[PDB]
Length: 169
Length: 169
Ligand SMILES: Nc1nc2c(ncn2[C@@H]2O[C@H](COP(=O)(O)OP(=O)(O)O)[C@@H](O)[C@H]2O)c(=O)[nH]1
Ligand SMILES: Nc1nc2c(ncn2[C@@H]2O[C@H](COP(=O)(O)OP(=O)(O)O)[C@@H](O)[C@H]2O)c(=O)[nH]1
Ligand SMILES: [Mg+2]
Ligand SMILES: [Mg+2]
Image (tube, rainbow over all chains, first blue to last red):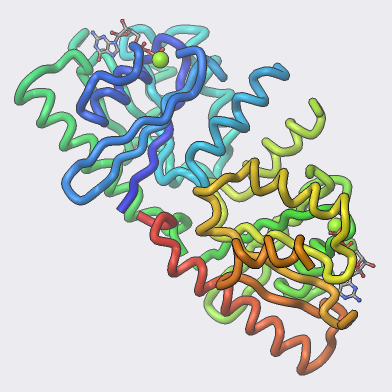
């Protein structure tokens, strides 16, 4: 069956890179418009929508168009945050994303940290919300490290999706 | 579990009336903005979003707001059409709705005819698309007729939703 994933975050967070890691190929450009791309993973079609710098008239059109790509809706919304580079304008984007989607959306949202290889109040506030539902990625990983991290990432997404008691009917 | 239903159609189609019939109480006004209302039906929470005359800047804001009400997405999108009163500007709305949502959306869309009690090329084109997935309502029905028609309507929605092979993961 089909697993629909949307990536949100500030420009420079690593959305497109994360999408590449999910899909297991370099297809997003690591973004002036929303792009939908697919892969086959085991018996699952992964459908990933990468988003441009959405977070006023032109943006609204593009938001509507982005939403229509994942109809009737996604299974998982991935908030992508760059470790180390999460400072002022990076948290300004996160508070707006969270205010926009609100409490209801929390059950299908997952926090993705990028720049794990480059290894705080703003980070601990995030973790108070997504403590159970988060992942750290090194999107530059290759070989076995890359394959292991992809499995762990898809495993989390599937876990959150199966647990979403307000997902399916 | 929760069953999320969105109503689309031209002003005067009977959206709000249909929503009342689904929810089993007169709560929509039979609409300047999207309104979300709920009922308990057996072990199911029915969540119905009634829409205003969406089908340019203000509309886009309101579309985004309408979409956020049913996050991550609806299970069923109900296209509401008034029998007898389906002429020129009524089909103009339908072609735009269908172009907007496109082929993908067809699997979760259901055709609802209103004004059954008031008992063609435009109608046969519709039926070529929704032959298996349609219902006719008399939203003025009371008593047993009302209860019978509500059961048949909820039964169709649940059927379409369980059959949607691109719905749940
Ligand atoms: N070192 C490192 N760089 C990353 C990682 N993820 C993304 N990047 C880099 O961060 C920059 C922005 O990435 P990009 O995918 O375009 O971010 P986007 O704007 O959110 O789509 C690029 O230089 C990427 O190569 C990571 O996990 N580690
Ligand atoms: N006779 C009859 N009138 C209906 C039916 N459904 C809706 N109406 C009437 O059609 C008019 C428009 O209905 P309304 O729910 O406000 O349509 P909306 O603009 O799509 O929300 C009102 O007069 C309703 O009472 C129906 O099944 N039979
Ligand atoms: Mg990008
Ligand atoms: Mg109305």
